[PDB]
Amino acid sequence: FDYIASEVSKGLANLSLELRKPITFGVITADTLEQAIERAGTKHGNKGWEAALSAIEMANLFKSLRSMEIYEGKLTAEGLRFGIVASRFNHALVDRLVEGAIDCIVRHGGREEDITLVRVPGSWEIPVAAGELARKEDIDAVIAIGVLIR
Amino acid sequence: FDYIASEVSKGLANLSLELRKPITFGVITADTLEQAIERAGTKHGNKGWEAALSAIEMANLFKSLRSMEIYEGKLTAEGLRFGIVASRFNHALVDRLVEGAIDCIVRHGGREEDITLVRVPGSWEIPVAAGELARKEDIDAVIAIGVLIR
Amino acid sequence: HFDYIASEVSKGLANLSLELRKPITFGVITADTLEQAIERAGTKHGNKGWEAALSAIEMANLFKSLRSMEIYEGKLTAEGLRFGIVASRFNHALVDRLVEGAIDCIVRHGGREEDITLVRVPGSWEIPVAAGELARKEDIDAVIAIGVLIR
Amino acid sequence: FDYIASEVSKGLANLSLELRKPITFGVITADTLEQAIERAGTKHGNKGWEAALSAIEMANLFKSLRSMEIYEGKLTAEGLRFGIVASRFNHALVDRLVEGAIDCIVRHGGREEDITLVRVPGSWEIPVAAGELARKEDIDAVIAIGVLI
Amino acid sequence: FDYIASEVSKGLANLSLELRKPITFGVITADTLEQAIERAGTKHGNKGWEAALSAIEMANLFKSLRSSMEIYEGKLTAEGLRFGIVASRFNHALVDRLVEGAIDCIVRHGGREEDITLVRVPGSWEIPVAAGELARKEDIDAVIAIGVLIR
Amino acid sequence: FDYIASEVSKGLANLSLELRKPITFGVITADTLEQAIERAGTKHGNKGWEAALSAIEMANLFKSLRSMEIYEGKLTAEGLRFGIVASRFNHALVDRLVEGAIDCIVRHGGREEDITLVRVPGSWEIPVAAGELARKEDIDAVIAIGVLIR
Amino acid sequence: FDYIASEVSKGLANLSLELRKPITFGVITADTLEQAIERAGTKHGNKGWEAALSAIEMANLFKSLRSMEIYEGKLTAEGLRFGIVASRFNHALVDRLVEGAIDCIVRHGGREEDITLVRVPGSWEIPVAAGELARKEDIDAVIAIGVLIR
Amino acid sequence: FDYIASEVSKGLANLSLELRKPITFGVITADTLEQAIERAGTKHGNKGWEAALSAIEMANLFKSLRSMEIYEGKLTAEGLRFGIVASRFNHALVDRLVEGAIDCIVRHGGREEDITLVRVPGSWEIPVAAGELARKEDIDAVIAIGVLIR
């Protein structure tokens, strides 16, 4: 449970730096399933909801980036395209996180036609699968959603 | 304390219903300054930030109102004008809430050019000032920011 | 501020009903513990949404027929009437239960889901101000307010 | 838990002040069942009887008003018009209260032809229902009858 | 209290299956008059109100019965339906309340008082035989039996 | 008791503000009989006497209103037309308070020809009864006399 | 509870004998709610699951029935049509019971389009509704599902 | 002592919202006379002094009201006209508060020729009396001064 968590963290960071595209680390790491529930305990501040919010800000920031000069990202998600990769194990909480992230995009102006969802068997395969979506020229940001119970 | 809080709450409610304009009650009431510090710094976001978010949703919902039909408020505030009333007493926390409210409105797309801010000396004078801002035609939402310490 | 909100909600809805001259049912569950809200949302015989919708149908028919001796009362045939439901978002797990119960009662009494307008609000404070617009719309015959207040 | 009781009391009082028309508050408030049963008895008469008597007295006072001048109303209700609004909850006692109220109006010279009765299912809907009869120009007095357990 | 209650329940059930027509068992069986008062006092409506509601639902269900899977349910719109009611006479203090509740339920649910037939019997022993005649009438869509059984 | 007292207080206050006419709140709110007896049987301390005196000062204030300027009401009751409403329930103390109020006005120069008395069956209908007396242009002040036993 | 349970059981038995069609008695009789929870807590298939299995076997038996010869029914659900009467009372447990019956029929190869489901208000109305379901020609087996709380 | 305090608070708030004119709530509510003294314990921060300061700011704010837009009131009280209503009961502290409020106006530039003082018998009559001054077109702000001992 330690190898997988370390590897996915390293892979996501390396992909983001190499490909120059925002990747959000929406991965739940909990030792107990109860704590994993509390990370998405019926609150609107779900892990997927917060990750989607950060992804929208990062994408808008890179659109402009690519007194003094101040750069920051808006939350206007309209006209943007996002990719989402979700793990399969323990899908009871995974589905909740996916719904929250999709809700955040739609509520802030995103369209479901520009949202691509990919499902993977295990969290170990998240980085390799997300690499394809990140390398796609028609993707502005990538959100990785998973759960790791120890 | 209790009487003042009751007066401002009923005053804002009466103004909202009569004037037909969304008004958010971003007034934090606490018996101890320690509780006020908790409700002002880094707990689940600034209360002014939360109140600004609620005001944005209500403003868009009213704009829309102007199977089964479902009505909901979009969180994008492009072209929506807002008015903020802030107390002066305990400006250490009041300025914190004003920072959160302005940050929410600006980062959600609303330009700061259309934001009007009015300062009042005490919490007792919030309803009367909001009575003028709400009666202005070019105001789409009113946010009241105040602190009540017992 | 549970007490302040509950008092404000009751006062606002009552004043709206008198001023706007249109029935507004108060389907709000006020509880201090989550268990009491679960008890009312468990549909042991019927949830408050079912009961509030039932009362609203009679009120709409009564005003339809009103607007020895004379006795005025409303029937429970909900066909041909349109309803406006305002649902809070806080504790939406129980709110969805109440909304489903109210819709079920209206549908079973001859109503159609096409003639039901649903409005979502973020907080209980925004229930009165949002409900006012639906009541002012002349095509709406009744207003149902559904919400939960936990202390 | 008395939010409904507070709302109906405030609504009725404000209606009377706004429209300048007498409204009688014949509502029994009791958290226990037996006290409501006692108030529906005949030891002091039914509350509907007392409410109807108050409406008659107040209506005559309004008609007369609109050494020291003294204004008071008689208990004769010939030729007047009354609007009675009653709830259905706990109708086992509400029916007797309504019967007593109508009995008082009829036996005090009033005619049932002018008695207009409005039926509501919940006590929350008493003020809004009264908003119609009270706004009618041909209603001399409004009576509100309800039970709150 | 024992034999009479068993016979009336068995007789109504046998008539319902034989004639294939809904028959509601609105019979209050109590060992003490206080229990009768509990079922006579308003508990979300009197037993007659519930019995009439059940009769309406069953009648519409039979009317329908005579995408993924066919689901049939009964609506509460009693328009154009004819009902027959049989009631006992003993303990008429509560019996009149029950029959008034049942009549009020049918009327307020869109039904017309013209299409309601009422038959009175001296004791509960004569309920099944009268119910059989009303059920065998072709112009009857449902039968409601109202009675009280005090031990 | 609680509902009746709150409604009477709010009703008289709203009528006074709306009609801009002085109205005195001479209502005894006691939980026990002895307390009301003390307040309606004080040695030269009748509440009706005190309420009438207050009405005299208010009327003299409004007649004038309608270094620095100072406005005050003189305690002379001459030339004032009063209106009095008296509850019928618990008439034992109501009559005492009415007599005390009449004594105060007459001993200050009031004429019984200028006092109009109206009786109300219950304390609930005091506000509506006083609402008509205050609406006559020839009435200078309104005095409400009532008793509330808990 | 005694009269209801006895009459329901007797009526269903008489209907089965008269109409010559399989009717299974999936009515759970309990004094308290604990017996209902344990018998519906997906132990190895609820009462509805078992009743559906019994109905399928009986339907297969009558398909062919209606040295020595031995007749028995297999556990195939293809080509068989079922009607289910479900009580509305305590629908929180009724849904689990009816779902178990549906799962047994579907997983035995049965198709959902042959299942006709009807809801009844009370347990007393179960026999009369079951009579119409069995009397229809296109119905092969009848399942009665109800909960009796004492 | 509770009815009077609630009624005067409601009356002042309603008058301010209805008439659109600043009204300052300089009313002392203390359970003990010692605490009432401490609210004006020889300090320059008296209740009347603070109320006058708030009144000056509110009046200047409304004069202008009737990057972004920021509105706030100055303390320049010159050329303004104020009305003061003071209760009579317990005048030992009332006179101190009145002197403090007058001192604040004069010290910040106000003139005694534009200050109108009205004295009322009891605190219950403060709202009705203040309504006249508030409705006067030659009054910019109204200050209500009173003491309530419980």
Image (cartoon, coloured by chain):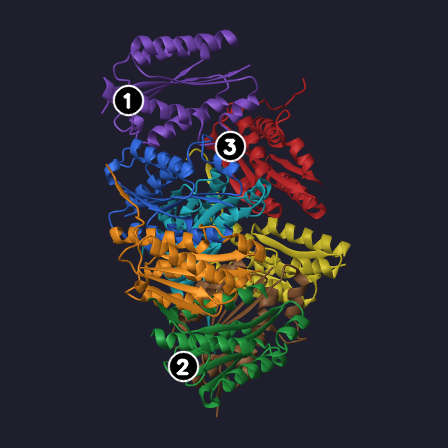
Chain colours: A purple, B blue, C cyan, D brown, E yellow, F green, G red, H orange
Q: Position of residue G99 (x, y in %)?
A: 55, 31
Dot 1: element: helix
**How far is the residue under mark 1 from the one under mark 2?**
73 Å
The one nearer the camera, B26 or E71, is B26
Q: Quadrant location of residue C39?
A: top right
Residue at the image position 37 percent from the left and 52 percent from the top: H53
Residue ID for mark 2: F139
Badge 2 and badge 3 both on one subunit? no
Q: Is residue F40 left or right of residue B53?
A: right
Q: Is residue D67 left or right of residue G23?
A: left
Q: Is residue H130 visible?
A: yes
Q: Chain of mark 3?
A: G
Q: Quadrant location of residue A60?
A: top left
The one nearer the camera, F137 or G147, is F137
The one nearer the camera, D2 or D103, is D2
**How far is the residue under mark 2 from the one under mark 3?**
87 Å
Amino acid type shown at disc 1 = Leu
Whether residue E151 is situated above or below residue G8 in the rendered picture: below
Residue ID for mark 3: G81
Q: Position of residue E127 (x, y in %)?
A: 66, 60
Q: Position of residue D51 (x, y in %)?
A: 55, 74
Dot 2: element: loop
Residue at the image position 42 percent from the left and 59 percent from the top: H99
Q: Chain of mark 2?
A: F
Image quadrant occupied by the N terminus of chain H = bottom right
Dot 3: element: loop
Q: Residue furthest bottom?
A: D67
Q: Which dot marks residue H94?
A: none
Amino acid type shown at disc 3 = Arg
Residue ID for mark 1: A61
Q: Quadrant location of residue D20?
A: bottom left
Q: How many other residues sit within 10 Å of disc 1, few (<14), some (14-19) or many (≥20)?
A: some
